[PDB]
Amino acid sequence: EELIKENMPMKLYMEGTVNNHHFKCTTEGEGKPYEGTQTQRIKVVEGGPLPFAFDILATCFSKTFIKHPKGIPDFFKQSFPEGFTWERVTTYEDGGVLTVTQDTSLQDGCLIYNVKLRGVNFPSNGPVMQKKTLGWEATTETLYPADGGLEGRCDMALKLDGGGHLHCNLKTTYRSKKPAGNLKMPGVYFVDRRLERIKEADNETYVEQHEVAEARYCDLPSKL
C-alpha cells in the first residue's frame, strides 16, 4: 500500500493454448492505481498471428489498479509487498471454456504478472474462432469475502460483427500471499469497469488496452 505509488509500471508474461494453438505474449504498461486507470501494450511474441479473437484474452492482462473509495478496504493494494494470485474459469454460452492462473508480485518497484491459460471447445464456426468480435461491453463484477480471499462473479458480453452479443460468465478467486491477519477485509462490493482497445496492429499481434475500474458498495437504501 505503502509500496503502491500514485504512478506504477507493470510487466506481464503470458503463455497459453486455445483450441490447441500455443502462444506467448509479453506486455509493458503503467497506470494510476488510486484513480483506477491503466494502460497495457501487448505483444504476441510466439505463435502469432492468433487464429482466435484476441478479445478472449483481454481480461487476463490487473486488480491493483482499481479505484477503491476510502470506506472500502482494498484487498489488492493491502496484499503488498507479498502480492496475490487469481484463478478463473470463463464459460462462453456456445461452449468455449477458458481457465487461467495468475501470479502478481512486486519487483524493483514494478508490478510483475505471470499468466498461464488454457482455452478449449470454442466452436470452429463461432465468432471467436472466426474472429468476428468487436470488443467487450462495459461490466460490473461482484466481489464476495470468502475465507480470507475474494470470490468474483461477472457476466460479460462480446460484441459481434453484425451487432448482437456472445455472452460468458467469469468465476474468479483472488487469494492474498499475505498472512490472514494484517488484512482488513471489505464487505460484499461491486467493481464497474470499461475495458477498451485503443490500438492494434498486424492482425492483433500488437494490442494496446485501456481499463477504467471503480469500486462501490451498493448505494440503494436498505429496509433491513
Image (cartoon, grey):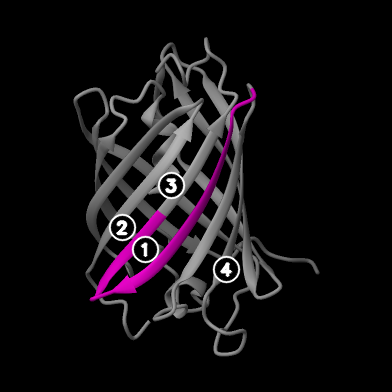
Dot 4, crowdedness within 10 Å: few (<14), some or many (≥20)? many
Q: Quadrant of the C terminus?
A: bottom right
Q: Amino acid at mark 4?
A: Arg
Q: Which residues are magenta?
A: 95-114
* Residue at position x 52%, y 76% in the image: 177
Q: Main secondary structure of the magenta part?
A: strand
Read off the residue under disc 4: 175
Q: Earlier in the sequence, mark 4 or mark 3?
A: 3
Residue 79 locus on image (x, y percent): 47, 78
Q: In 3D space, how far apart are the residues under numbered discs 4 and 3 (Cα atoms)?
A: 16 Å
Q: Earlier in the sequence, mark 1 or mark 2?
A: 2
Read off the residue under disc 1: 65
Question: Was residue 100 drawn as part of the magenta stretch in this picture?
Answer: yes
> Is label 3 or label 2 in front?
3
Q: Quadrant of the N terminus?
A: bottom left
Question: From this viewpoint, is residue 137 visible?
Answer: no
* Residue at position x 27%, y 61% in the image: 10
> Element type at marker 1?
helix
